[PDB]
């Protein structure tokens, strides 16, 4: 089933702040804001953890779109191959979720990777979820138009928190 | 000569809807709309199948331009290499035709891949045509300024429909 | 020294038309127009051949910038690697000169590949010049801020025309 | 510790001019101007060398952003891999510092490679500094939100000047 990160890293505070640092030309900013809130909320409603949005400076969870090298040890690689990545809870880069600007992202109304599903998978990592062996789980290692957390996802996040 | 898809998939309804979901900066939207209609019509006039254009939501044939990964298992790969792809008739991704935004497309007045020819080849796949061994056929596996369906193309599409 | 193309292809008419089909965001259109004229003129003043500019349809020498695949059998390849190519005199693609939009081009006032030098090298091919073994020649196989045709370049073009 | 370039190239004049030739869409021009001044000044305050900014033509130190091939023998390579490069003091390309437009650069307020740190490392090369074996040094070979020259950096630059 589900998995966590080596050593079960998790957010230790009752509240975790997040910030959408950069956006994509593929969608309106407000759309990304709403979808990010929804992705967070689907994990959030299952656990004793609260998220607070900030719009400047540093937050526990820094979310953004970027092309190529962007300040961490995992530069993006253009169209295709890697699509996004996120880091387990912790200080610094810990918890951050990055999306490769060189793909095509959609709110479901156009062609593209479904951003809501992608954000839910990545933010799952940002909360401490590893990959699942259950094909129905959002945390399954491979990639949406209509979904919800699977029982395995809920079981895993509740186990961690 | 011509070929179909393994198991002869084809549209079973008298009418098939299509939608141009995303466009290219290389051309005016209306130009893409017209060229898509023409490509469809060249296959359409030869068979008992009708196409209806829609401009929102899902249609049987979803047509669009995209860079990199875009929601299916065949992400685009930047400039060069793969130029486009389309799927045989069926539910979901079936029938869809995608074009790589990282190439240069033309209506024939500039440098670029001839979009009308490319669309006619891809939509051929969207209708259930495989590749032909006849060099004169639009469905020949390799890539326009002035063409029409070859006798092999017509023979194949009529055989399927 | 200099070389021509296998079989000495050359323009057989007294006048050769040319058209700048597509431009680059790196420079003003008029700048590209002027630099192209200058590149042509440096070869032109040495031979009994005249060039006439056209701004629509097809011309003997079609000049343009493009990203990735663009209608011929040599798609561009993104930043780096191939920078441009041109074809020996002849019908169709013959004589055409293409420049990869994924590099940086300059009129000499910024960072970039010197477009005047690049255009002079490519249009050399468009006129029937092959590569030279003389390092001073514009037609040397490898890549400008201040130059003129070398004696080898002049000797070669005059030999062909 | 620190290293210089083979043969200790260095600026021999009391004053060295610099010009920011091209900018990045990632940041305001003035921001790049300020950060470049700061990077120069951190090396400058430690040595008997003065920098003068120019805004046209050629300067000893030409600074700029570029995609792909850009006029030297080291074309950039798209997102990832090489991020930037600079040349040791000397005529022509000597002293120049180039940054790959295909990455993401930041002033520290967004996602991206920290431009101030990157500029300080590259301009270090432009002044004649090689790579250091000291992990605390800005000149360490690998890649920022809050830094200053390390004692090794200062020792090295003072040794050269
Ligand atoms: O997200 C992933 O799993 C992998 C790499 C990765 C990120 N965080 C990790 C934590 C542990 C191990 C690996 C990772 N990125 S990917 O580009 O291969 C990717 C894989 C799966 C999905 Cl669902 C999506 C997306 F973008 F759609 F969310 C992206
Ligand atoms: O269209 C093609 O054949 C191949 C891959 C492909 C798409 N659908 C298929 C169905 C079956 C088998 C392969 C395919 N794309 S390609 O990029 O190699 C390509 C090949 C041929 C042409 Cl004509 C064009 C274009 F874009 F011009 F239409 C593209
Ligand atoms: O122009 C070239 O030689 C090669 C490939 C090529 C084009 N035409 C040819 C005719 C015969 C043989 C090879 C070629 N392009 S390249 O990108 O390797 C290139 C090589 C040299 C120069 Cl000078 C420039 C530029 F762009 F600056 F003009 C480009
Ligand atoms: O800057 C570097 O070291 C290498 C290549 C290089 C440039 N100048 C050199 C002089 C000698 C030897 C190698 C180099 N560029 S890199 O892209 O690998 C790179 C390496 C380290 C840093 Cl810190 C940064 C940046 F951009 F952040 F400044 C870039
Ligand atoms: Ca963090
Ligand atoms: Ca990617
Ligand atoms: Ca479909
Ligand atoms: Ca491609
Ligand atoms: Ca021609
Ligand atoms: Ca290239
Ligand atoms: Ca210099
Ligand atoms: Ca790069
Ligand atoms: Zn990242
Ligand atoms: Zn994952
Ligand atoms: Zn696709
Ligand atoms: Zn095909
Ligand atoms: Zn070409
Ligand atoms: Zn050449
Ligand atoms: Zn450079
Ligand atoms: Zn370095």
Image (cartoon, coloured by chain):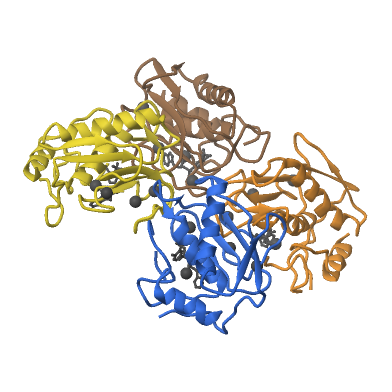
Chain colours: A orange, B blue, C yellow, D brown
Residue D21 higher or lower than C102, as above or below: above
Is residue A68 in sight in this rendering?
no
Residue A29's x, y, as percent?
Answer: 73, 41
User: On the rendering, which quadrant does ligand 6 occupy?
Assistant: bottom right
The residue at the point 50 percent across, 76 percent down is B157
Q: Is residue B49 left or right of residue C23?
A: right
Residue C50's x, y, as percent?
Answer: 17, 35
Q: Is residue D38 left or right of residue B2?
A: right
The residue at the point 65 percent across, 62 percent down is B52
Residue B39 higher or lower than D157, as above or below: below
Q: Which residue is nearer to you in this view: A34 or C142? A: A34
Q: Is residue D93 left or right of residue D26?
A: left
Quadrant location of the C terminus of chain C in the rendered image: top left
Question: How many numbered markers are drawn?
Answer: 0
Question: In the picture, residue C42 is in which quadrant?
Answer: top left
Q: Which residue is nearer to you in this view: D139 or B12? A: B12
The residue at the point 74 percent across, 73 percent down is A135
Residue B34's x, y, as percent?
Answer: 54, 53
Residue C143 higher or lower than A146, as above or below: above
Residue A144's x, y, as percent?
Answer: 74, 63
Q: Which residue is nearer to you in this view: A98 or C6? A: C6
Q: Is residue D29 left or right of residue A95?
A: left
Quadrant location of the N terminus of chain C in the rendered image: top left
Q: Which residue is nearer to you in this view: B4 or C102? A: B4
């Amino acid at each position: 089933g589900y998995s966590l990160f080596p050593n079960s890293p998790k957010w230790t505070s009752k509240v975790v702040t997040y910030r959408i640092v950069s956006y994509t030309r593929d969608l309106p900013h407000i759309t990304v804001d709403r979808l990010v809130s929804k992705a967070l909320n689907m994990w959030g409603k299952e656990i004793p953890l609260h998220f607070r949005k900030v719009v400047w400076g540093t937050a526990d969870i820094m979310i953004g779109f970027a092309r190529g090298a962007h300040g961490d040890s995992y530069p993006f690689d253009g169209p295709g191959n890697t699509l996004a990545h996120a880091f387990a809870p912790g200080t610094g880069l810990g918890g951050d979720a990055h999306f490769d600007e060189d793909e095509r992202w959609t709110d479901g109304s156009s062609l593209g990777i479904n951003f809501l599903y992608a954000a839910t998978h990545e933010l799952g990592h940002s909360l401490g979820m590893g990959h699942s062996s259950d094909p129905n789980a959002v945390m399954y290692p491979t990639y949406p138009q209509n979904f919800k957390l699977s029982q395995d996802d809920i079981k895993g996040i509740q186990k961690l928190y």
